Amino acid sequence: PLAKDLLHPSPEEEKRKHKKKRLVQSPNSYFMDVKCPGCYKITTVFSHAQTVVLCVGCSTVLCQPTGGKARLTEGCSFRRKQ
Amino acid sequence: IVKPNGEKPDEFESGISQALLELEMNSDLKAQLRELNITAAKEIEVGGGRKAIIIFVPVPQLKSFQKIQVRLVRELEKKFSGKHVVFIAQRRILPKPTRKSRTKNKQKRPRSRTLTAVHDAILEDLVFPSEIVGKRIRVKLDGSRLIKVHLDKAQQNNVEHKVETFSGVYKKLTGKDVNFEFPEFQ
Amino acid sequence: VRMNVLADALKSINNAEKRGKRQVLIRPCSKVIVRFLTVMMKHGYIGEFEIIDDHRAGKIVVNLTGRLNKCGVISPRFDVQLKDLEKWQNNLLPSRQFGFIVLTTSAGIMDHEEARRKHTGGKILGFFF
Amino acid sequence: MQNDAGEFVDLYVPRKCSASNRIIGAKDHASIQMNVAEVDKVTGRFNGQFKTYAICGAIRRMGESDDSILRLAKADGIVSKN
Amino acid sequence: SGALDVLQMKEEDVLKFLAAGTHLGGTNLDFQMEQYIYKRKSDGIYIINLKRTWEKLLLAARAIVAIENPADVSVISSRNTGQRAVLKFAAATGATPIAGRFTPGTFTNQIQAAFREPRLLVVTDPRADHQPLTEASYVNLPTIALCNTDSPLRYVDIAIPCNNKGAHSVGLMWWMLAREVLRMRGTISREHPWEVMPDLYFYRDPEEIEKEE
Amino acid sequence: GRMHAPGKGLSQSALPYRRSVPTWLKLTSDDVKEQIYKLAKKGLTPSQIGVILRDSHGVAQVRFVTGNKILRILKSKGLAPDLPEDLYHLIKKAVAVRKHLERNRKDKDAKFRLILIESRIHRLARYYKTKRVLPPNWKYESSTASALV
RNA sequence: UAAAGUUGCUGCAGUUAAAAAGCUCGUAGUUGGAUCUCUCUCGGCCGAAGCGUUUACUUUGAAAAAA
C-alpha cells in the first residue's frame, strides 16, 4: 500500500467493495425479463423483489421474496437488462 | 418558419430553417418537424480546419426533438459535408440574487435556472445518444479546472470522432475546458 | 453526528500525510473544502486534486506531496479582525517565515497574507504549515 | 537557508526520503542509501553509473521499503513496466 | 530488467523455476507480498508470479553489483537449507558468508571477534534470519531477502518473491543471483550457459548422502 | 447510528448514477401516473406504491420517469392521507403496544419500548407541525391515538 | 499579581494517582451534511427619488472630558 491509486481502482476491487463504499456508488441489483411457458408477454422483475410477482398469463407465481435476491421460479428464463 | 428568441434572424439561422422546412416535406418525419420548432443556430470553429453547427431548440420540445434528432442529425451532416450538428436547449440563466439588486426577479430563482444546473443540462444535451456515466473535475496546479466526462462504452466508436467538437461547443457556450473518455469498467 | 465537514477533510489529509501516503480520499466534498484545498495548493503544500462527482455529494482524491507538517481547522470560526490577526499567527504558526492562516472574508477565502494585502479581516477557517 | 543577502547559512542540507520526501535525520541509523547499478542497453553490463535511493527508517520499519524501492525503480526505468 | 531483450527471462530459466518449485508459495499471504503472487490454487497454495521474481532478482543483482568491494556484501543463512548455497555464492561473487548461527552483536559491537561492517545484506529467510535484519536497522545496512508468500517485509528493501522452503528452490535462487551478479559485473557471458550447475548450490541432507554411497 | 438503538447499520438503497429512464421501461409518464392513482385507490401508501412499481411493472425510480415524487403526485391529484405515512405507522405501533400493555401490565419492556415509540412520534409531530403539514394544535394523546385512526 | 498549563477561552484532568451519573428517554441550552455565478438626480459628464430585500461578520467614516 502507501501508494494505492484511488482514482482508478480495478473493476474487480470495485465490485468486491460494498455498494455504498465504492468511489461512485451503484446498486448490486438489476432488472430482468422473465419468459414463462404459460405466457408470452414481457414482465420485468426486480432481482431483489419483495412482492410475489404473478404471471398474468397463467396461475403461477413468478418469484418468491427472500432475504436477499428473489427466488425465481423453475422453468421461467430470466434475462438481465443493461 | 422559425421563431427567433432574440427578435433578430440571421443569414445562417434562416438557412438552417430552410433546410429544416425542406426535410419536413421530402422525408419520413412530416409527422415530426411540424411543431418541432427551433429558435437559433450558430456555426463555430472547433479547432483546425473543422467547424460545427449548434441548433438551439426550445426547452419544452427538446424531448420530442431528442426522439428524432439522431435521425435528423445524420441527414444534416450529410447536407453540410464535414460539419457536425448539435442540439442544445435555450436554457436561460437568471443572475444570482444579491443584496444590492434591482427589479430583476421579485420571486425566488428556480434551481433549473441557476448557472450550474443549466450548464449541466447543456452538457447532457450536447451528448444526447451517449449518456453521462461519470464526471470528474481535476483542479490543476495553476488553479485551472478541467472536466473529464465518461460516456457510454457501447457508443464509443460512433462518437469518438464527435469529440473535439463537443469540447469546442462546450467551451463556446459555458467557457469551461472539458474532455470525454470511455472507461473500461462499466 | 457529522458537523463541519472541513474538519473531517483536514483531519483526513493530516492523517494520510503522517502515514506517508501519496493520495487521500476526502468525502464529502464542499465549496469551502475546495477553496481551502486551492489555497493550500497555490503554495505548493498539497499538489493536484480531482473532484469525483457522484450525484449526491462529491468526493475528492488529493495527491500528496510530503511537504505538509500539519493542516488543521479552527472551530468555532471566530470572526477575526485585521488588528487581531497577528496574535492569531502567533498562536498557530511555527515561525514568521512560513505557515499560513486561512480566513474566509467578504472578498473570498485566502491566507492571512492576502487578507492583510487586501485590508480585510474575516472568520478563521484553519491553518496549514 | 538564505539570509536577506542571499548567503546560505545552513550547516548542511539533509537528505530527504526518496519515497515520502521527508527529511532523514542525522541519527536515523535505520535509514539506507541504496545504489542500483545501471546496465548497458545492448550488453546488459555495468556502466559504472548507478542511481541512488534514500529510504528513512520509519518506512523500513513499516515494511513498505520494498514496495518503495520497487516503485522508484519502476518510475526510473530500471524495472520494466508491469 | 529495464525492458531490455538481453536481460529478459529466458526459456531455460523458466524451466528451471518450474522444476525447482520456485513458483509455489505457501498457504498464507503477507499483505506486503500480495503484489508478487498471481493466483491462489484450489488447495490454498499461492502461485508466485515468476516475472516479478525475475524483476526483483535482477534488481537485487544490480544492488549487489553497485557495491564496489565484493566482500562488503554479506550473505547470511541460519537455516541449513541455504547454508551451502550461501557458501558457493560467496565463492562465486566474492561476498562474505555467514552460514549457521548469527551471533548477536556482529554488526553493532565494535569490540567483538567477528565484527563486520557490510554495505549490503542478503538473507535467505526474513523469518529465520530476523537477527541480522533487525541488526541492519542499527548500522544503515540495506537488505535483500528471499521472501515467501508469508515472509514479513520489515527491514527488507529488495524482496525476491520465491519459494525459500524447498532446498531445490533455495539453491536455484542463490545460483541465479550469483549468475546474474557475475553477468552484470563482466565476468562470464550471458551468451553461453554458465558452467556451474544449479545442483551445486542445492542442500543435501545426510540421508541422501548415505543413500548415494 | 439508530435514534433509539445502539446499532449502526449501513443497509440502505444505492441509487445508480444515471438519472435517465431505463431502456426496458416503455411506460410513459402519464401511464405511470395512472398506475400510481390506481394503486392508491387500491389503498396503498407511497412506499408500497413504489415497491409494487419497482417489482412487477418495473421502474427504477418513478421520480425519474414522471419527474415528480409519489406523494407529490398523490397530493397533486389529491389522494394523500390526512397524516403522513411514517407518523401514521408510528402511531399504529404505539396503539398496538398500548393494547398489548393493557393485558400485560407486568411487561416492563413493552413500557420502555412504548416510551421510545412515543418519543419518536413526538419528534415527528414537531417536525411536521413546523413544516405546516400538521395543524399547530395537532397533538398525540393516548386516549385519542386509536380514536383518531 | 505572576510563577499557576495547581481553574486551563488560548490551555488542564477523569482506566489504575481526585474524578464518567447504574441505565435509557427527554425540554430549555449548545451544535447541526452537499447544493444556487424602468437607481445612476431639470436646458437632448450637470439639485430631486427608499424595507434601496431585514441581519451577524468584516472594513471605512462621524461622535466620543481632562488627568
Image (spheres, coloured by chain):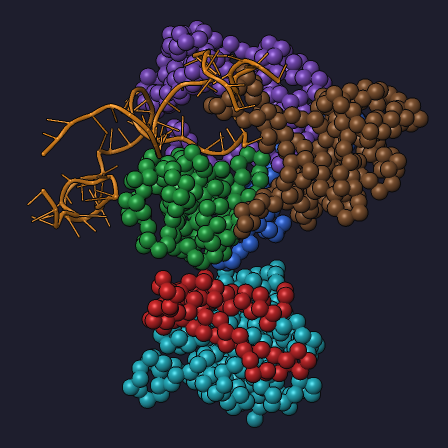
Chain colours: A blue, B brown, C green, D red, E cyan, F purple, G orange
- Work out whether residue C8 can be spotted: no
Where residue C89 appears, as percent x and y from the top left, is 31, 47
When the figure is inspected, residue E206 is found, relative to residue F121, above or below; the finding is below
Where residue A57 appears, as percent x and y from the top left, is 77, 23
When the figure is inspected, residue B52 is found, relative to residue E112, above or below; the finding is above
Q: Residue furthest bottom?
A: E213
Of the pair E194 and G60, the residue shown nearer to us:
G60
Q: Residue at x 87, y 26 (%)?
A: B18
Is residue A10 rendered to the left or right of residue D10? right
When the figure is inspected, residue C118 is found, relative to residue G45, above or below; the finding is below
Of the pair E50 and G32, the residue shown nearer to us:
G32
Which quadrant of the figure contains the N terminus of chain F? Answer: top left
Is residue E148 rendered to the left or right of residue G21? right
Q: Residue at x 41, y 9 (%)?
A: F136
Where residue E99 appears, as percent x and y from the top left, is 44, 84
Of the pair B125 and E72, the residue shown nearer to us:
B125
Is residue A18 rendered to the left or right of residue A41? left
Where residue C12 appears, as percent x and y from the top left, is 43, 47
Is residue B11 rendered to the left or right of residue F138? right
Q: Residue at x 58, y 35 (%)?
A: C55
- Asked which quadrant contains residue E76, the reply is bottom left
- Work out whether residue F4 can be spotted: yes
